[PDB]
Each structure stands twice: as structure tokens, then as C-alpha cells.
Image 1 (cartoon, rainbow, N blue to C red):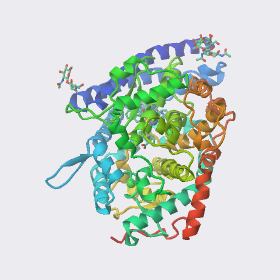
Image 2: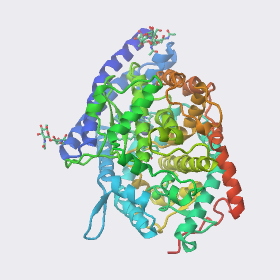
Image 3: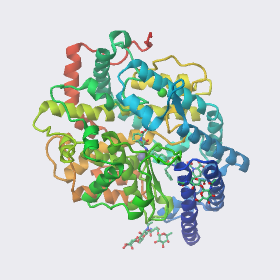
Image 4: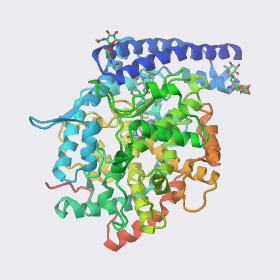
Length: 586
Ligand SMILES: *[C@@H]1O[C@H](CO[C@@H]2O[C@@H](C)[C@@H](O)[C@@H](O)[C@@H]2O)[C@@H](O[C@@H]2O[C@H](CO)[C@@H](O[C@@H]3O[C@H](CO)[C@@H](O)[C@H](O)[C@@H]3O)[C@H](O)[C@H]2NC(C)=O)[C@H](O)[C@H]1NC(C)=O
Ligand SMILES: *[C@@H]1O[C@H](CO)[C@@H](O[C@@H]2O[C@H](CO)[C@@H](O)[C@H](O)[C@H]2NC(C)=O)[C@H](O)[C@H]1NC(C)=O
Ligand SMILES: O=C(N[C@H]1CCS[C@H]2CCC[C@@H](C(=O)O)N2C1=O)[C@@H](S)Cc1ccccc1
Ligand SMILES: O=C(N[C@H]1CCS[C@H]2CCC[C@@H](C(=O)O)N2C1=O)[C@@H](S)Cc1ccccc1
Ligand SMILES: O=C(N[C@H]1CCS[C@H]2CCC[C@@H](C(=O)O)N2C1=O)[C@@H](S)Cc1ccccc1
Ligand SMILES: [Cl-]
Ligand SMILES: [Cl-]
Ligand SMILES: [Zn+2]
């Protein structure tokens, strides 16, 4: 009967709110205070939430969702039938929870030490070395050292993690954990759709890569850069070479049109982490969207503690499943890169507030890419030179074609360079999960993809025992990655649509949607759906059509594509890395 199924979902919602709120609290308390005691409590709460998931999931599987008429009830029940790791026998469940905590903790406490010298943490110390050092050997020390300490230490856990996450997936009716993850998109054509989008971005990426490679050749020397080969992976300003904008100084298209040092401007003008989040809050409310609650300011961790606590620094946003308590945990540094991250995280909080009155089972983004995209959309407007000048972080840069191309390059170094990285991470993990890549070949297959998609090579040959994927947060934390590929594509579609709704004319990259209530309304209507409808409906509400499409990103960067093609042709660049086997001689 429809009536027993409606009652079931009402009971599930009531009880899940309580249990999920308790689990979220214990998880937060460990993430913001890594201790033996908080780990023990977290593992205990893990068994408590598993008992609830098993109880209600077992009930849900007694309903034949075929017979169910109401589609929202059918949708909730189908979801609750997936027990996730609560499908595991008790011993394997305890083992999985411990392995996950061990991997997460290992990553978040790893340090890289000089001999009889200081020990560096990833945030801020190694991040700053990668961003600012311009000495090959110092960058190599940080790049190799991080992999030696964090990556190699994850390897002992990863095969058993794979076994257990796959076992749970099979117990819930999937073939492996990658199948489970991909199912979040409810899109049978997902793999083909993502491949087509990746291929559309190749002209831009290959041209950007060749131009940056030439600039690296100029700085690091002809003996260290092959103009027809892959780029050494430690030279791009970022530990993972996933975003390249920190080497803007090495690649600036028009050096005669310099930009104000934004870090020094933020520091000289007294910006703090709290100010950064307040500015993001102001952008959301300028669109008519919701302010974060007072409680957010009391309870969030917006900077690394100075009091002796060890924490998980990697920035993240937290819903406590009570409609009131939402928090960010970020070890914020005062610079423009982290201002963008603060917007990314504030977008999650906005989504949490928008869907807070849906049943908890539907309190998720339309798909995981939508969740990661919202804050980045607003940050596209914040990042415009006009907006940054309004914040007194740049001088006036308008009315200058040189400044225009410089800005597009700054944006491409992050947004375009990230496309191949974000594509490859779960290409690797899906093949680990499906058994195509074994522990014998984890690292070799990672580097084959880093070459194939990003055109990068490791500066030091890898050795048996290396596990470089473990040195990237999302791997030991079991956070899917294709969401970020989707996000980077769709955030430009959203920007284009919101700019049109705001009445902007002229080139897309000049748009700033600040204060547009029409733009806010598009976003709010879509976010309020949560996970209640197939994601093409939310896509339609924002953009006027239902597909994912690279057209908006291509339009944004069209003037830079034209500039890059002319520049690369002038210098005779060979796009790609036809000398694909090249690696550094020294
Ligand atoms: C299929 O069932 C859904 C879900 O119904 C809700 O959840 C069930 C478990 C039961 O507890 C129901 O009693 C309960 O309504 C129906 O969706 C719901 O429809 C109602 C009626 O339009 C929506 O009410 C609105 O609520 C807002 C505030 O939240 C008011 O301001 C509005 O004026 C309006 O009254 C409700 O939001 C909506 N809920 C969800 C989660 O979608 C759905 O109508 C039903 N389908 C059919 C064809 O009957
Ligand atoms: C970090 O975690 C430790 C361990 O849970 C906290 O110390 C506990 O604090 C509670 C309440 O303050 C006491 O009831 C326990 O007896 C304490 N346990 C130990 C082993 O000291 C500590 O307060 C936490 N720090 C922060 C800043 O939250
Ligand atoms: O993405 C996430 N959670 C995903 C992880 C990848 S798989 C996916 C599909 C199958 C069911 C369930 C499973 O893990 O088994 N599930 C998840 O929880 C976290 S970051 C955000 C989120 C939280 C709650 C609900 C939805 C999203
Ligand atoms: O997404 C996240 N954090 C950001 C912070 C930096 S910006 C952003 C965009 C670029 C791609 C990706 C990157 O840095 O690898 N990324 C992030 O990881 C968090 S909300 C993911 C998470 C969710 C729940 C629990 C734990 C983590
Ligand atoms: O939300 C996530 N991961 C969830 C997936 C859905 S189930 C949930 C409840 C039971 C315990 C635990 C489990 O069984 O894996 N768990 C998860 O890890 C990831 S994406 C985000 C995240 C990562 C690290 C710390 C905090 C958040
Ligand atoms: Cl790597
Ligand atoms: Cl995903
Ligand atoms: Zn995020």
C-alpha cells in the first residue's frame, strides 16, 4: 500500500535526522581535534549510524518499489535500500571504518622534515613552497618529500580498502564501488558524455600546455624542459599540478600590463579569514540568497588552530542535518586563491540552507557536480578585474586589451588546466575498483594517465613502494572526484545563464553578477529541488536547457584560444607530447 510506504519514509526521516546529527558532531569533533579519544568516539558513532542504516535499509528492501505510485516516496525508498558499508558483516564493517580513519589521519598529520631542521606540514608550508619557489631542486624536495611521507604511508591500507568498499557495493547490488559512485548521476551515458566534454576542451588545453611549457623552458633551462615532451610535474605552482595559476609570474602574456600583488594588498588592508567569508556571505545575499546563520560564525573553524590541536586542514563544508547548524572547516590563508576556496565552501552552505526542508534522503545536490559548482559560479564574478578593483585588491585594469588577455590567462591556468586532472583521477579509481588495475600496477597506471591526459611526467622516476595517488586528499578520504570535472564544466554554463538573466551584454568573461536578484532566483529555484528530481530538471531551471555542455566554457575562453593559437604558431610549437616517453635526465 502507498500508505505503509509513506509512513515508512516519515519514520526514516525523523530518526535519520537525530542519528545523522550525532554522527556529524562526532566526525566534526575528530576532524577539528585529532586525538585518541575523539577517534574512539567517532568509531563508536560509526557503529551507531550503521545500526540505523541496517534497520531502515532492511525495512526499505521489503517494499517492491515497482508497485509504488507516488514517485517521491518511490525515490526515497529506492535510496534507503542501499546500505552502503552497513551491508558488511560486523567484523568487516569495523575493519573498514578503522582503515578509513587510519588513511585520513595519516594524510592529515604527515610532515616533511629537513635533516636536523624544521618539519613542514602540507597546509600552509608545502603549499607555499610549491606556489612561490622558483628553484627546481627546492620544488623537487617538497614534491618528492610529500609523496614519500604521505603517499607511501597510504599504500599499506589501500588494497584492503578496495576489497571492503567493493564488497559493500556488491552487497548493495552494484558490480563494484566505481559502479556505485557513477550511479549518483543517474545517467546511463555518463562515461560517453564526459569523454565528449573532455575532447571538446582539448584545443584549449593543448594550446595552454604548449605555451606554459615554452615559458618553463625559458625559466628552468633548455636542459630541463623538452619542448616536444611532457612537463615535469613539480613546476606548475601546485602540489598536484592540478591548477597552474601560481606560476602566472612565469607566463604573463603582457608583462607591460602588470597586476597589483593581491596577497600583499589583502595583508596591507587587514583582510583576515573571517573577512573573506563575510565577503562571500555578502555576495550570496546581494543575489537575494540566504545569509549564513549566526551559529555558523560561532561554530565554524575558519583558520588553523594555534592552540596545539591537530586538525584535518583540507577545506570542507558540513551539514549537521537539523536545518540550523552548518559549518565550514578550512585552514584559511589570506590570499586570493583561498578567497576563491572560501566562496566554493560557502556555496555548499547555501545549498544546505536551500534544501533544508526536504526529507534528509533528498538533501543532496541535483548531482554531486552541482554541489561543487555553486560557490565557484559566484567566484567567477568576484575574480573579474572590475570586482577585485572594487575590493581594492587590483588597480584599474579596464580599457586594455593587454590586461584582458592577461586576465583570461590567469583564469585559464586554473580552470582549463584542471580539466584533464579532474578527468583522470576517477578514470584511475574506476579501474582500481573494477579490478583492471591491481596493487602491482597502481602507481604505473596513475602515471600513464598523468601522461595521457595532462601531458606531465614525474621529475624523479618512481620506485616500487611509491603510491602517489595517496598523496592527494580525496584518495585516502574516499571522496569521489569526477564531481569536480562536472563542476568545472557546468559552472561556466551557470555563469553564462545568470549573466544573461542579469542583462549583461558583451564578452562573457567581463560579466559580474553582483547584486542581481534575477540571477539569485535562478539558482535558488534549482537548489531548492535538492535531489528530488533528475538533475536535468535543475539544469533546465538555471540555463533554459537540460544538457551538460562545454559551449559556455569555450565561449568564455574564445579570445584566449585565438591569442594562444597565434602565439604558439609564431614560435612553432608542436602541440601535445609526441615525445611521450621523455623524462628528465637530471
Ligand atoms: C508524492 O508525495 C510527495 C511527498 O509528500 C510528503 O511526504 C510524504 C511522505 C507524506 O508525509 C505527505 O503527507 C507529504 O506531503 C508529495 O510532495 C509534497 O506535496 C505537497 C503538496 O503540494 C507539498 O506541499 C507544499 O509545502 C510547502 C512547504 O513545504 C508549502 O509552502 C506549499 O504551499 C505546499 O503546501 C510538499 O512540499 C511536497 N513535498 C515534497 C517532498 O515534494 C507529492 O505531492 C506526491 N505526489 C502526488 C502526485 O500526489
Ligand atoms: C580535544 O579533544 C580532547 C579529547 O576528547 C578534549 O579533552 C576532553 O575534554 C572533555 C570536555 O572538555 C573532557 O570531559 C575530557 O575528560 C577530556 N579528555 C581528555 C583526554 O583530556 C579537548 O577538550 C578537545 N579540545 C578542543 C579544543 O575541543
Ligand atoms: O559523495 C558523498 N557520498 C556518496 C559517496 C559516493 S557513493 C554514493 C552513492 C551510493 C550510496 C552512497 C555510498 O557511499 O555508498 N554514496 C555516498 O554516500 C558525500 S562527499 C556527500 C553526500 C552525502 C550524503 C549523500 C550524498 C552525498
Ligand atoms: O571540495 C572540497 N574541498 C575543496 C577545497 C579546495 S577547492 C575544490 C575545487 C578544486 C578541486 C578540489 C581540490 O582541491 O582537489 N576542491 C576541494 O577539494 C570539499 S567541500 C570536499 C569534501 C567534502 C566532504 C568532506 C571532505 C571533503
Ligand atoms: O561523506 C563522505 N563519506 C561518507 C559516505 C557515506 S556513509 C558515511 C556514514 C558511515 C560512516 C562513513 C563510511 O561508512 O564510509 N561514511 C562516509 O565516509 C565523503 S564523500 C566526505 C567526507 C570524507 C571524510 C570525512 C568526512 C566527510
Ligand atoms: Cl602525483
Ligand atoms: Cl562524483
Ligand atoms: Zn566542495
